[PDB]
Image (cartoon, coloured by chain):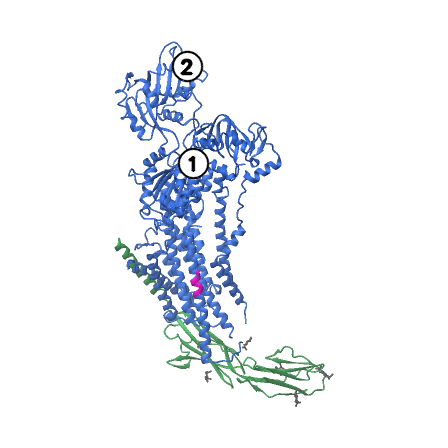
């Protein structure tokens, strides 16, 4: 009958707004059942063609999962990197030319090994991330009760719902017996909702039946139900990673250009020289071995040019940082998530659970004619009053509500019953006076005239008859109802005095109004002792409900967490804008937003509900357009009555927007299932640890293990440290690759001999530099990082100070290495390694050049500790054992390589004074650093 | 005694012409079973046949080819005849050390190898003031150990004042002569002290800057 999209659009209405709609369009529910060709009393025929036709039209109740990518296919995707392709080709041609004899296979083989390293790491990272998000039976389904799997349900079914059931699909309410449902999976509020045809007939998928029984007619079944929408929006690289990939690609292509120029220059010079002077016969005998040597030199320029071990260095720095962040109660689930929050420009935050404690709590009190803005001390007031209050609340309760142990780590006690009553049950205990035996004195069997919830006045009262024949009445209820019916105020230790207007009008506007303006619900308790003849008719009560003795008035709220306001103030000083996106009504949302600091009463912002938001961002054909979101989102601060789709739409609109000229990075904090989509769409998502709702846990990037909002501040500062650490490595590594190239190029042109070999530089790029990265990652973060603005999403990555340092240090290294090349044999009184014959043994000249290069980079690891303009690069160096251990280990391995490396490394052993001169030259880099730290980068 | 007529002796020059050596068994009453060529007493490969009259050809005569060749005839019941042809070439030095670096108080060794026939005479010399002059053994430390195609000059207890220099080895025959040079360098014992002091300077400078900066 009705098309799928029609019913799906119908199922997005709640409350009385649904009821009228139905009556307008599809009459009563027994008519909409007829339109689906189903009978509420009979049920469903169960015939196979009917069932299959319905499954074809409206879909099935089953969502197929997305199979995960395999490690082999991740390796195959890792192999398709351009930087790896050029290196594989170079290694192949090197191993090829090696076997033209008319151990030269080491070099090419070494290159392959480096590739086999990088891939095996990169794939592994891509694997672990895939493994984090992997997480993302029978019901009575007929009038004639038949247990059927949930996947077999079809639109038009008649289902029966009882206590404890979890609803399998969206539907409508035919008939029942006092249904109360828990819809926290969709709204995030843990309140029981009463389902009746006149009030609210909509039943939704995934919600939990708290009380009652009934039967329903299924309307949306598969990916069209609310849980299906949530899982569709959950799917079922990074900002820094994108910047790094772009930089690596352009460095690689610069290296290719330099290698090609080297080869063509060598070939052209050879040809021109030979055919000018010799003019030998054109027989192509010699004439081949020269070309082989030219191609080997051209491959060497490429190998020294590119940073082979950059993914390894980034991975090890990020792993160290994650390990350290764990102590600040931030569980980072995958590596590349530790940086994003450093540059976030916005936070969209859930209210209940995240910014509040989600416990109904008495915050303010009016007892003894003294206002308590804070809970008083035990026995700080009349003991008779305290006993009477405790007994009143406990006995008046008379209901199944109890308080329970946390059952978890660092969790609050769990309130199982109605919220308000549990508020007072916790208040009596917060007075440091135990109530457990008082109630147990009177079992509910020894009980009398009780009217529950008193739908007339919504004020609940009881009578109790132990003390004497004079039976005692205990009544609690809303202030607006109960207050005027009271006649006595017990003030202090003194006896209760009579009051009336001007004796109750003064507390109004001095006590009640401030409480109501604090967003507090007001509940007042009263008692009577009258020895009158027993008249517990349940119909003669109106005369009884007067002359109350009002003992107190309390204020109950869901209170803000203690540390939220200061954390929000710190986050705003860092250049971040905080917005509230909640599923609760707008009054509570706005009150909590004022207390938390999100809105200051300046009245220049937007507070909206979900309906207005959805309507105002759509065209005449009812589809979302970015240009209309760009008007709402810049000044929106509170969004209330929002579904999962509204949260997802808002975060998507903020991320995609091109206004404001500063492109946005968005973080989302939440603890509920309805926050699952947005937590996934956000650049970084935070989930509350103890208050799990595990779906929010697998959707999130970071878990706050203590439910502390201040941890988010510690996540900004840590994220601004990780960034710095990587820009300490980039300054170091880019100084190596530049110098090497200018040495490998020039040496090739003039001397045609390759002063820096390929294995020599695969040791430097692969092994030495990843440990340099780990050493440079080890400074601890400080709060002074919270004093700077967020960086742009497309900032260059290489600042002006980094450029100044790279060029100023390359000048020193290049002038000294060229001095060594051209006049080094005279200074050290040795013989030259220049223009060496074919397959000649290693040299001390070129071993001194290599060892000096490595000493200069080793002492530049210390200079790379400051990326701004600070002089003192030794600040904290001796406090750090990892840095010193790594530097000494690198020194020892270099000694072993030079002394015992042999031909494979192209090293001949050096004397002691030659080592001392290498160390002298390398240590002059720390003095050149103090020279160039004087130059102001503003020039 | 069987009579063998042999070809004339040949001097290998820089010419690339092949050279053919001949042996003729002009008189023999004994039943020969075979014959073979030898160089320096070592039999050349693939040189045994009937070959009552036998020939050996060198397509690319070089200095390494020159030597004292023999053409041996082995008979059933007669002693072998080893008639000999000499192939003369100028000496060619095929081995030396480019440089010899040692510490004072140690001992140094320098050597030369050659390829020629007849085996050359060896003489060592040292460049003094532009001209090579004979080694003077006034110290008593020099130890020349000449040999047939090898020669060594060994020095014990090196002195840093006079020993460092350039030493030439000369090999001579009736045809020509070949000489190559080596460099000897002696290192001072206080060599690692000058860099070390320099390091002590650098550190001091660094300290001052930071101590003045704060
Ligand atoms: C020596 O042997 C060669 C090669 O058989 C021959 O041509 C030549 O006539 C011989 N000479 C004499 C004198 O027999
Ligand atoms: C070569 O053959 C001839 C003819 O039989 C014979 O007289 C002579 O002894 C042989 N020389 C050898 C086998 O060396
Ligand atoms: C052949 O015998 C003679 C006998 O005087 C000897 O001098 C010569 O060295 C021998 N030839 C070879 C190759 O041994
Ligand atoms: C040099 O004199 C020493 C003194 O004993 C002697 O042993 C050595 O053989 C001499 N060498 C030469 C080449 O005269
Ligand atoms: C030099 O004489 C030695 C003596 O055994 C010999 O082994 C070596 O082959 C000779 N070298 C040359 C080039 O004649
Ligand atoms: C030394 O060697 C040179 C070049 O080989 C040669 O000209 C000279 O005659 C030699 N000195 C002699 C043989 O005394
Ligand atoms: F109460 Al909520 F998102 F958890 F509005
Ligand atoms: Mg919540």
**Chain coloured blue in the rendered structure:** A
Query: Which quarter of the rendering shows the C terminus of chain A?
Result: bottom left
Residue B157 appears in the picture as rendered: no
| Mark linked to residue A106 | none
- Does A490 lie within the magenta span? no
Q: What chain is tagged by disc 1? A: A
Q: Residue at the top extreme?
A: A533
Q: Is A700 left or right of B22, judged from the image as shown?
A: left
- Residue A165 in the image: state x and y as whole percent: 52, 30
Chain B: colour as depicted? green
Q: How far apart are marks 1 and 2 (CA)?
A: 48 Å
Q: Is residue A447 above or below residue B102?
A: above
Closer-to-camera residue (A469/A734): A469
Secondary structure under badge 2? loop
Which of discs 1 and 2 lies nearer the camera? The answer is 2
- Residue A162 in the image: state x and y as whole percent: 52, 28
Which residue is disc 2 drawn over? A539
- Residue B62 in the image: state x and y as whole percent: 55, 81
Q: Is residue B88 above or below residue A860?
A: below
Please state the extent of the stretch shown in magenta in the rendering: A252-257
Which residue is disc 1 drawn over? A690
Q: What chain is tagged by disc 2? A: A
């Amino acid at each position: 009958g009705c098309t799928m999209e029609e019913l799906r659009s119908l199922m997005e209405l709640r409350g009385t707004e649904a009821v009228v709609k139905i009556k307008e369009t599809y009459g009563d529910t027994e008519a909409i059942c007829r339109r689906l060709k189903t009978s509420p009393v009979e049920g469903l025929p169960g015939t196979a063609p009917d069932l299959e036709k319905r499954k074809q039209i409206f879909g099935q109740n089953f969502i197929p999962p997305k199979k995960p990518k395999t490690f082999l296919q991740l390796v195959w995707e890792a192999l398709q990197d351009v930087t790896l392709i050029i290196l594989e080709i170079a290694a192949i041609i090197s191993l090829g030319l090696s076997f033209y004899h008319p151990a030269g296979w080491i070099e090419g083989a070494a290159i392959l090994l480096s590739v086999i390293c990088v891939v095996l790491v990169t794939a592994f990272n891509d694997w672990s991330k895939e493994k984090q998000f992997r997480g993302l039976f029978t019901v009575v389904r007929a009038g004639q009760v038949v247990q059927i799997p949930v996947a077999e349900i079809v639109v038009g079914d008649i289902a029966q719902i009882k206590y404890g059931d979890l609803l399998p699909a969206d539907g409508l309410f035919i008939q029942g017996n006092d249904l109360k449902i828990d819809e926290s999976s969709l709204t995030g509020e843990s309140d029981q909702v009463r389902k009746s045809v006149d009030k609210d007939p909509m039943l939704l998928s995934g919600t939990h039946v708290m009380e009652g029984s009934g039967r329903m007619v299924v309307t949306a079944v598969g990916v069209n139900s609310q849980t299906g929408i949530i899982f569709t929006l959950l799917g079922a690289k990074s900002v820094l990673q994108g910047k790094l990939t772009k930089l690596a690609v352009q460095i690689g292509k610069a290296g290719l250009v330099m290698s090609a120029i080297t080869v063509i220059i060598l070939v052209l010079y050879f040809t021109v020289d030979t055919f000018v002077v010799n003019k030998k016969p054109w027989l192509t005998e010699v004439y081949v071995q020269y070309f082989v040597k030219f191609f080997i030199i051209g491959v060497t320029v490429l190998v020294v040019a590119v940073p082979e071990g950059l993914p390894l260095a980034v991975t090890i720095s990020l792993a160290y940082s994650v390990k350290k962040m764990m102590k600040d109660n931030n569980l980072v689930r995958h590596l590349d998530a530790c940086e994003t929050m450093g540059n976030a420009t916005a936070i969209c935050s859930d209210k209940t659970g995240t910014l509040t404690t989600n416990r109904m709590t008495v915050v303010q009190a009016y007892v003894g004619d003294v206002h308590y803005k804070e809970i008083p001390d035990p026995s700080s007031i009349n003991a008779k009053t305290l006993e009477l209050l405790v007994n009143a609340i406990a006995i008046n309760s008379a209901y199944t509500t109890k308080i329970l142990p946390p059952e978890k780590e660092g969790a609050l006690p769990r309130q199982v019953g109605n919220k308000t009553e549990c508020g007072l049950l916790g208040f009596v205990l917060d007075l440091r006076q135990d109530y457990e035996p008082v109630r147990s004195q009177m079992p509910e069997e020894k009980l009398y005239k009780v009217y529950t919830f008193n739908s007339v006045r919504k004020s609940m009262s009881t009578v109790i008859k132990m003390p004497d024949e004079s039976f005692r009445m205990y009544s609690k209820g809303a202030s607006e109802i109960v207050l005027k019916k009271c006649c006595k105020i017990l003030s202090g230790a003194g006896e209760a005095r009579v009051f009336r207007p001007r004796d109750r009008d003064e507390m109004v506007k001095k006590v009640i109004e401030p409480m109501a303006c604090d967003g507090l619900r007001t509940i007042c308790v009263a008692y009577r002792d009258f020895p009158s003849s027993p008249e517990p008719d349940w119909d003669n009560e109106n005369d009884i409900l007067n002359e109350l003795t009002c003992i107190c008035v309390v204020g109950i709220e869901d209170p803000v967490r203690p540390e939220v306001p200061e954390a929000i103030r710190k986050c705003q000083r860092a250049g971040i804008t905080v917005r509230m996106v909640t599923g609760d009504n707008i009054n509570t949302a706005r009150a909590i937003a004022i207390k938390c600091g999100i809105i200051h009463p300046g009245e220049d912002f937007l507070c909206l509900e979900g309906k207005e938001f959805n309507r105002r961002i759509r065209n005449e054909k009812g589809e979302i357009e970015q240009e209309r979101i760009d008007k709402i989102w810049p000044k929106l601060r509170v969004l209330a009555r929002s579904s999962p789709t509204d949260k997802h739409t808002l975060v998507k609109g903020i991320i995609d927007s091109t206004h404001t000229e500063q492109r946005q990075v968005v973080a989302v904090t939440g603890d509920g299932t309805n926050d699952g989509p947005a937590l996934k769409k956000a650049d970084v998502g935070f989930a509350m640890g103890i208050a799990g709702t595990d779906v929010a846990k697998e959707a999130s990037d970071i878990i706050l293990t203590d439910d502390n909002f201040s941890s988010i501040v510690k996540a900004v500062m840590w994220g601004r440290n990780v960034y710095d650490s990587i820009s300490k490595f980039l300054q170091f590594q880019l100084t190596v690759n530049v110098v090497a190239v200018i040495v490998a190029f020039t040496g090739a042109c003039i001397t045609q001999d390759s002063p820096l070999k390929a294995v020599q530089m695969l040791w430097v790029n692969l092994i030495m530099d990843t440990f340099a990265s780990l050493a440079l990652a080890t400074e601890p973060p400080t709060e002074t990082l919270l004093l700077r603005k967020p960086y742009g999403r497309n900032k260059p990555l290489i600042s002006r100070t980094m450029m100044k340092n790279i060029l100023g240090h390359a000048v020193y290294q290049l002038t000294l290495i060229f001095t060594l090349l051209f006049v080094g044999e005279k200074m050290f009184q040795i013989d030259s390694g220049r223009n060496a014959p074919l397959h000649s043994p290693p040299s001390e000249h070129y071993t001194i050049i290599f060892n000096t290069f490595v000493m200069m980079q080793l002492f530049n690891e210390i200079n790379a500790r400051k990326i701004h303009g600070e002089r003192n690069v030794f600040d904290g160096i001796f406090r750090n054992p990892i840095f010193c251990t790594i530097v000494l280990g690198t020194f020892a391995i270099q000694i072993v390589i030079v002394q015992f490396g042999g031909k494979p490394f192209s090293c001949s052993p050096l004397q002691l004074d030659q080592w001392m001169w290498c160390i002298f030259i390398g240590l002059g880099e720390l003095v050149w650093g103090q020279v160039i730290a004087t130059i102001p980068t503003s020039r | 005694k069987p009579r063998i007529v042999t070809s004339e002796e040949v001097i290998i020059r820089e010419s690339l012409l092949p050279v053919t050596l001949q042996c003729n068994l002009t008189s023999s009453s004994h039943t020969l079973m075979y014959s073979y060529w030898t160089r320096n007493g070592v039999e050349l490969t693939a040189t045994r046949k009937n070959a009552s009259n036998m020939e050996y050809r060198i397509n690319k005569p070089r200095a390494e080819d020159s030597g004292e060749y023999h053409c041996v005839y082995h008979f059933v019941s007669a002693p072998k005849a080893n008639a000999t042809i000499e192939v003369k070439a100028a000496p060619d030095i095929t081995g030396h050390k480019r440089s010899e670096n040692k510490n004072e108080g140690q001992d140094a060794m320098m050597y030369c190898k050659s390829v020629g026939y007849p085996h050359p005479e060896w003489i060592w010399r040292k460049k003094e003031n532009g001209v090579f002059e004979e080694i003077s053994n006034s110290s008593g430390r020099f130890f020349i150990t000449n040999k047939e195609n090898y020669t060594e000059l060994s020095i014990v207890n090196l002195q840093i004042t006079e020993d460092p220099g350039e030493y030439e080895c000369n090999a001579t025959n009736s045809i020509g002569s070949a000489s190559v040079s080596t460099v000897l360098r002696v290192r001072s014992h206080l060599a690692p002290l000058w860099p070390f002091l320099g390091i002590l300077a650098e550190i001091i400078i660094l300290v001052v800057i930071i101590v003045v900066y704060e």
